[PDB]
Image (cartoon, coloured by chain):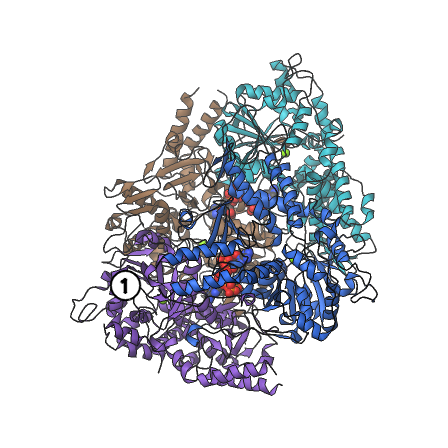
Chain colours: A cyan, B brown, C blue, D purple
Amino acid sequence: TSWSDRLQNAADMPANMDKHALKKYRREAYHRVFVNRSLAMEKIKCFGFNMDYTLAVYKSPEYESLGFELTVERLVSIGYPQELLSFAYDSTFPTRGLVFDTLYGNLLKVDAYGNLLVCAHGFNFIRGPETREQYPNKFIQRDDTERFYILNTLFNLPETYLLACLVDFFTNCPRYTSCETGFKDGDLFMSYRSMFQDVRDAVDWVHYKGSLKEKTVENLEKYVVKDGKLPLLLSWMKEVGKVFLATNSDYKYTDKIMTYLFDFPHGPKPGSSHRPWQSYFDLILVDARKPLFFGEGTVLRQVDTKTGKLKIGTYTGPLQHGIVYSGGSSDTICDLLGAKGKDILYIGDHIFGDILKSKKRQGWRTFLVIPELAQELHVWTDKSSLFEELQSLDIFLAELISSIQRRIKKVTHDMDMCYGMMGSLFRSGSRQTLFASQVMRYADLYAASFINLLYYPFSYLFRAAHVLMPHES
Amino acid sequence: TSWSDRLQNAADMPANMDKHALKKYRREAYHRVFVNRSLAMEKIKCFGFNMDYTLAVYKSPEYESLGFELTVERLVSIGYPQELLSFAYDSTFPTRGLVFDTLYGNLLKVDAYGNLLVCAHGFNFIRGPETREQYPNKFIQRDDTERFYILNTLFNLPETYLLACLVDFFTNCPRYTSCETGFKDGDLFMSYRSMFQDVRDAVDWVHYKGSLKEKTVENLEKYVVKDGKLPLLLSWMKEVGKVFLATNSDYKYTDKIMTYLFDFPHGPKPGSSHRPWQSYFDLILVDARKPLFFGEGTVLRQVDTKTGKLKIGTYTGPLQHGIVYSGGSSDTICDLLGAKGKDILYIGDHIFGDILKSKKRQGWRTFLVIPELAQELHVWTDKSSLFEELQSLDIFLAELISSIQRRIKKVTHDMDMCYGMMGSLFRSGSRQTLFASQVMRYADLYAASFINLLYYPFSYLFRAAHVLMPHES
Amino acid sequence: TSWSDRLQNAADMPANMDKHALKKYRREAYHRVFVNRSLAMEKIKCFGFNMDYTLAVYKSPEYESLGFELTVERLVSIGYPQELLSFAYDSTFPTRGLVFDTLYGNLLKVDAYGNLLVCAHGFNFIRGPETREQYPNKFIQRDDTERFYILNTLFNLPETYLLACLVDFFTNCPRYTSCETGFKDGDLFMSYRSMFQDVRDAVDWVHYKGSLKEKTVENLEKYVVKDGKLPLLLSWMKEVGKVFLATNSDYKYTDKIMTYLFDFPHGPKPGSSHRPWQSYFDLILVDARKPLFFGEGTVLRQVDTKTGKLKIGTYTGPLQHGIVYSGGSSDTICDLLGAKGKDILYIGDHIFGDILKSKKRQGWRTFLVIPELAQELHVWTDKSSLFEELQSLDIFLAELISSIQRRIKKVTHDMDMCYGMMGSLFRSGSRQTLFASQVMRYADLYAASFINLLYYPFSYLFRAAHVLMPHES
Amino acid sequence: TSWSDRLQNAADMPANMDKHALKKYRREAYHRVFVNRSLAMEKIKCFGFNMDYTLAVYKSPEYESLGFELTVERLVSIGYPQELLSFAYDSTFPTRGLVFDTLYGNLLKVDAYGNLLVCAHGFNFIRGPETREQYPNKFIQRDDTERFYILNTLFNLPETYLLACLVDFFTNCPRYTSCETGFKDGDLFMSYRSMFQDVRDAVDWVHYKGSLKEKTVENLEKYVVKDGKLPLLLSWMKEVGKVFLATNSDYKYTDKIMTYLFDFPHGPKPGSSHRPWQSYFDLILVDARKPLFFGEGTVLRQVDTKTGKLKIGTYTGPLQHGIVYSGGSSDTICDLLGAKGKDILYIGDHIFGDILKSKKRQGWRTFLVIPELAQELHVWTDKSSLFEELQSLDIFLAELISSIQRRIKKVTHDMDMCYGMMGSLFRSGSRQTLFASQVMRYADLYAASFINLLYYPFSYLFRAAHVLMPHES
Ligand SMILES: Nc1ncnc2c1ncn2[C@@H]1O[C@H](COP(=O)(O)OP(=O)(O)OP(=O)(O)O)[C@@H](O)[C@H]1O
Ligand SMILES: Nc1ncnc2c1ncn2[C@@H]1O[C@H](COP(=O)(O)OP(=O)(O)OP(=O)(O)O)[C@@H](O)[C@H]1O
Ligand SMILES: Nc1ncnc2c1ncn2[C@@H]1O[C@H](COP(=O)(O)OP(=O)(O)OP(=O)(O)O)[C@@H](O)[C@H]1O
Ligand SMILES: Nc1ncnc2c1ncn2[C@@H]1O[C@H](COP(=O)(O)OP(=O)(O)OP(=O)(O)O)[C@@H](O)[C@H]1O
Ligand SMILES: [Mg+2]
Ligand SMILES: [Mg+2]
Ligand SMILES: [Mg+2]
Ligand SMILES: [Mg+2]
């Protein structure tokens, strides 16, 4: 049971319009919207969306496995060994938000301060004392972006596992010699950095020149969650405000995906005429190039929606019915919708490119979709006994000799393994991950899906407790 | 009663060595060490210090007023009008951590997200609706470091007030025309940006080429807090670990100041022989050039302590008794003391250049000295009734029509004015400042003075509660 | 009769081995090697080559016209108007080395100092006084590389004409409004800068992703000069020194082209066994990425010559028979051949990327191939009467009222038109072009083809007269 | 007899106004203006000047020796050894335009292509074969500006000799160990790069914070050439055009120097009323910051000529009588004088900062003053027999075994030594220097002094022969 099984299960249910039914459906943790900073929904005047993994939630593990298979086949195509074709995607290994150390070829799970929580070389999990040889302070410099790459997105899940697969394969294949910073093959030396770049280039290629999009759109039921409540919720948003789309994807792909998402024999509610997906948006913008979008952006272009090509030249005209934009900047949206930043609730899945950047650069209000939360919540509530025991051990030790520390490490591991080999997205034991810290800092609201907004009235006041400093308590 | 009066009051008392006396003296909020993240003191192997406003705490408002007077006289010297000499430093106006907007000439107090809490043009405090003309989203882009300058340090307090003085003077002087981005004087236009640069250059000049240091060292009793407990605490640190000094100041000034700080007719305790200040340090490093120090740093030099000049060449030798270093990098300290980052507790007063940077770049443990906390604590506990009323108003409104909002704004202002015209260092009403957020994020421990460590045993476990995400609660 | 007709005519003749026959064949200006700086051939130990337009001389105007047609069809493919398909390449318009001014959409012919010699907007040649509106000092800043693009190569000849075609088309097409910096089409504004970028991108695309290479290799007789003297001369070079190839092209294309160039029923001389083209080289390097090659270069790779793919990893081994390199740097060649810069004569056609950069960065000796010289020489000797008259007019005026200036401008134009609409590669009248100045400064030797070296003994001392300053004469 | 003795000798003579007297005085090579590119003086509408070493020609070797002594005393002041005080400036060693290699501590004389002509380590002149260890291709990369510093100016002559003095001193002083890249002194290593930086910093300090200016202005007869013909020539220029001053020096120094230069008991001619120096200029601009001046420049300021301080603010007004500008850009001059680049003859002594940059960035006409030419001409004409013999040897060898090469090297050295230990500014034997090449390329006119313009009518056509390519001859 993957997180997308949970979402597609909730998606299959009819949308009860009764006001008591929505407020009661809101009880389950799975249907809740979580609040890091208070937000008065009545002040929101524009609802903004990205598409991928927000409106178009790709089914797991089928879509990761497709991306993994095409990336492997691209690497074999450029000259990697045929043994790569015997890899098979394993959804139990990767957790999102890991850091690949391109110097030593390690996947690292770190906290907000660069402290090491988990270190794996290939499929070998390196224990505390052994990591100190490569990480003397059990710490990485996050600003060393040439060395460390943060695997922020769900699109990065196939390459997260692929990187570990490759390190494992070259380590144990007799043809190659293992060195500290790569692998030697006779007169050829492949550094982990160059291998990582090949992987990155191949993932990009699969998405932009390969067949991933084509294979997705030829079997949309297999790869994309479809929910009749999505048109309903978007129609409610457009009744109280303006609605816009700003996606990094191109128009031809967006049109195919969005058409599928809205292909029901009715409009927002059963019995209503079907409307085209574009009619749900006051402003549609593709090729957004986020996060650069939230700074200078790019030249504003207009899409010829008949051919799917860009019209030649910079678009200098006004917002018109049926126009589709390409490129531009976040200021394009604000000017054309007559919005200020805090009037906008932007719903995205990219913690860095959508949420952090719109918050810091423009002061937009933010809603982070976290697809895996649909299943991490289930693990969290089911295995809560282990966390409560861990909390007790931390408290008992905080007042105590060392037989407790071995029990702390033991329960930490058992808790983490319920999530997978790389543990929870949000923590390792009692230590929070970098990802959790960035969710708390930059996502005003968050949920497994933005559809959970259906269960709250549009006057709702999302409330978070005020923060106090230690000396103020 | 300034914050330095509080510190000098506590400094004048004898250090009772009784173990029950120290743990009981620790009760008062003023003698406490506050904890943002848990820290086991037994793991600390090196105690590091800066000098200015940490070991050498400059008396307020005398030192700010001296800096203000010399900066004004430098500006008049380069051609600013004689009316500047009628300014007089006013300690009730500036709060530390304000942002000067060089485009519009405003002092801004902002939260961690760039939201405006206070805006003053000269001495005119701009009310909410009027700020929207210049700040349409009541928000500044903090990454626009060419436009916004954060006045982080206590050394910036004179220029904080001076900037407001200058804007006020040119606005109301009939010879000048007020424009949006500066002042016009016939065929001369002085932008707020160029005026700000003149101020910055003059403050730098006063510290590095003018007479500020000379005037300080010729009346040390007037300008520098002296505490007999400082040699005592440093001697205890050197009994359990190593102690180092890394100051941005030069050796000749450091030697004069430190000699004064240790000039008592005894050593650590009354009855003991006096020891030179240098004997309290395993490593002394001047001209540190923090924060660059925590990256590549500069070439490591050796001070000729007889002449006070640098020896010619890069120092390639080892740590030796009596050597004094200049420049280098944080790695110099780690290598020479055989320390890893988390072995080091670095005690500093510069939230950015000492604390944020050593934490993020090197994973050092951090102790932030906040001199004004000695008096902000007194205001906080005395006027606690206003904050509790403010908390009630926020709760009552969070469940309610708009007669409460005017009461919220009214109590916010009355609370803030107890701290001064620019309010608390840490908040405006219920909203925390950028400075408060950076203290919580990067200072593991903090206190009005590091001397408060005297009241804790060196095995102490400083404890902070574990953080949970909203969905984990 | 194009310049490549001249070369292919000389190519069709048998190579007479008689030593008196070669030294006599050297009399014609067309078979000479011209000398800017003295060069003793006996000191040359390595002969280096690029491939395109040096070993593989593409026939004119067929190859330019092919490149023009595919670039036009790529622009139409991305959305440019169908009228582009009615353009047809005209070899009489473009001269190499022109500067496209992306601000005003002009093709400029300039001297070494940025002075304007010719200015054309579309097909309209702007006369002296009219250029002063856009060029007040009849001068461009050559360091403004964001505004001015120098069309250095023969590959740039199709886009030189295409840029003029496009400016002409949009100017005179009623659907578009002509503005100073581009063309307006309703709500779309296309700047000359964005149009220029589209052209550049399309030319790149045609060469790297389109069908230009495929169409060339499917009709090599139509597109590539073939000379039996090329294997002969290369074999003589390998008898006295080492021979290397460093091409920006990839191995699969290089192999196809070079195989064709060496496909004769014999080896160097008639009657000898045929040898593969690779056997003529001590070192073969593709994907050179010149001019970056002459600085840090790129990682050194090894080509799998069976598949045409790069082997995975950096090549760390030695120079071996049959190895083919990819990337690397000029230091790769020097180290592997045991050469110093002045031991190397590098034969190239790119005045900037081959000749200027190897000379300035590495002190290599240089031989510039200038394909058009084969025909510019014929025009120069035939129409010499006009130049001599021009020289007389300059002398007579230099001692004289203004009826001479109109005659000077008149003869200048008549002389220039013999070369084409944009005049000689090397001058406009008595003023030398930027290109001529860079040939003189950075090409030690030059010729229409490097095959002219066949007519000189390998002990030859190429001689240039010593330069004196004015005060030394 | 120094070059400034020649200039001061010519300066002491009365200015005969007879038109035949001026055209006859023009015969001597010493009074001629030399021409690299033709220039019609009637087209010049503005005459521009720098001050230092153009209007204010500092006497040699007294001024170099003063600069040397103060720089040495500054280095001793910061901690260099006392033995430096026994150095004494030697005008026979330095030639202008040498390159200090900061890696190996060598002074290099190079040609325009980076080829080594002379190499000296300290006072040891390294012979051809021995230089190949450090310079394998007898070549330096001029674009490696972090390694190589070109000593372009007459102000650099003291540090040219000082650098050789220091290398010589540390090499032969027993306390220091000689390494390839510097000197070791126990645990201190001083690289040639850091030593070079100390020298550079000290020269800057002497000019901007030390006593060099003060000592110059207290003995102007000792240090500055004074010529009654200078006011005369400037008055003739102002009769036919506009005259401007753009100096890097500050106003207080400029005023002192210019007052001295114009302090005669008469105006332009004997018998005329004296006029203040400022009245000879249509535009006076100080603090020019050339060469940045010829790009974006700096903010335009106005000097308060009463106090010598800058007025506060950017000057936005027009050109007015008596105004003195500070900063700005070359566009300031063009706009205020209504000039285009080719209307301007700019007379400067800095081959890079005045001449190269105004020519390339702005297309100004250029006149380079070369003070040493006053004496290099005398050596050139006196020792012409050696050069003619050298030319014969080159011709005889160019048609010849190796007994001639030793004679070529022998005569080259004897010729060079007549100029000094580092040879002619313009050549070593038959090889031209980088400096000579840049004079020819960027100086339209040149002379030992701009005063030589007095001997030419303002309608004069300076003529240079047209350049032909080898294939055009
Ligand atoms: N999740 C992320 N993915 C990719 N890049 C990131 C992410 N978070 C931060 N960055 C960028 O990586 C660089 C290094 O980050 P840095 O060490 O400055 O931490 P930071 O982003 O300031 O986080 P914090 O303020 O919590 O320390 C920064 O320029 C930042 O913008
Ligand atoms: N207190 C400070 N004083 C001066 N500069 C600062 C301070 N805090 C951050 N900076 C620097 O200012 C620049 C702009 O900061 P930015 O907008 O990235 O916020 P940040 O430092 O990442 O804070 P946060 O992560 O809390 O948003 C950054 O490069 C940062 O290093
Ligand atoms: N033929 C060329 N094609 C492309 N770029 C060039 C060419 N010649 C020079 N450049 C580059 O263009 C930039 C601007 O050149 P710049 O104005 O400095 O002239 P330059 O190359 O120094 O020529 P010169 O020394 O003759 O003035 C330089 O960085 C230079 O390397
Ligand atoms: N006389 C000089 N003094 C200082 N810098 C110079 C001088 N001449 C050139 N430079 C600068 O030094 C850098 C390196 O020069 P580079 O190797 O490009 O030669 P260049 O100036 O283009 O000369 P050329 O065109 O004759 O080769 C350039 O950016 C150039 O502007
Ligand atoms: Mg998305
Ligand atoms: Mg400090
Ligand atoms: Mg080529
Ligand atoms: Mg000068």
| Residue B265 in sight from this viewpoint | no
**Splitting the image into 4 quarters, where does residue A431 fall?**
top right
Asked whether D240 or B319 is in front, the reply is D240
Q: Vertically, is C29 above or below A423?
A: below
Residue A347 at x, y percent in the picture: 59, 30
Q: Vertically, is B435 above or below B217?
A: above
Q: Which residue is mark 1?
A: D237
| Residue A156 in sight from this viewpoint | yes
Asked whether D43 or A468 is in front, the reply is D43
Q: Vertically, is D415 above or below A198?
A: below
Q: Vertically, is B164 above or below C270?
A: above
Residue D402 at x, y percent in the picture: 62, 85
> How many badges with numbers are in the image?
1
Chain letter of disc 1 in the image: D
Residue B1 at x, y percent in the picture: 35, 45
Question: Horizontal placement of C316 versus A326: left or right?
Answer: right
Check disc 1 and give the amino acid type.
Met
Residue displayed at 52% across by 83% down: D392
Please state, as top left, top right, bottom left or bottom right, where the N terminus of chain A lies in the image. top right
Would you say the beta carbon of the disc 1 residue lies within 8 angstroms of ligand 8? no
Asked whether A328 or B381 is in front, the reply is A328
How dense is the environment of label 1, judged by Cα within 10 Å: few (below 14), some, or many (20 and up)?
A: many
Question: Horizontal placement of D440 versus D403: left or right?
Answer: left
Residue D86 at x, y percent in the picture: 41, 82
Asked whether D284 or B306 is in front, the reply is D284
Q: Secondary structure at mark 1?
A: helix
